[PDB]
Image (cartoon, rainbow over all chains, first blue to last red; front, side, top):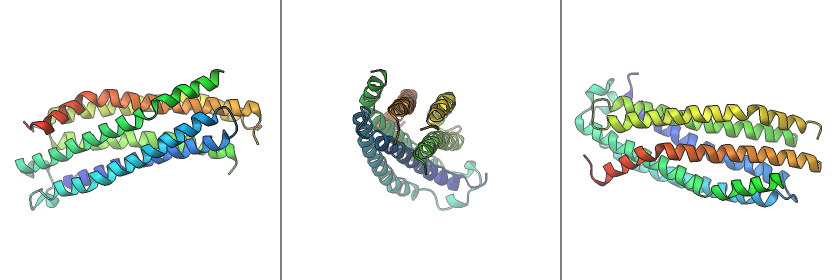
Length: 134
Length: 127
């Protein structure tokens, strides 16, 4: 590829989009199960998970809405010709530090998302299992 | 749409979204690993690339493994308001996907923890 900065820009956008699509798809499926489980002994667990995943979805939306401006703000620091560079060897040492700060930011978002998505979900898997066996 | 068709579609979209998320994470980490070669970020970027590749392939195995089980359950529902027996089948289906969700997030988080720690440390005091 001859558009390294544009590729990173696209890659970040696609990652954030895929993160939100995953959160919405999780809630959507759990919503279908909650509806079918109405008045059954699975309803409590399915309803609790629906509420957890709605909140995880909201948190993910907030985390992604907050990283977008942070990322854009950081990338203004790239050197003047950055959008026209065709090879990473043209980047300045300062440009590498700018991209490094973006990288660290993305890693922290990924870590925080996974931490939040999981912490809320752990107790419902057990209730789901308890209702299947008895 | 039919409720069983809607659930079949919901499960397919959920599993697809999980694997697309993994692939998008890998793709972005690949780009970073390339742009950081020979810089002081290359070690962490290469480690993260290896981690996210591992997680993507683990998620791929995990989701392929449940394909036959889910198929078997939804076909037990083809005959099937749902009967009480249908509700129990749907409960096992729900449990199966909840387990995939929990296992995926648990594994992805465990695997990224070390590189995440190194990156946090770099934010505290850059090298």
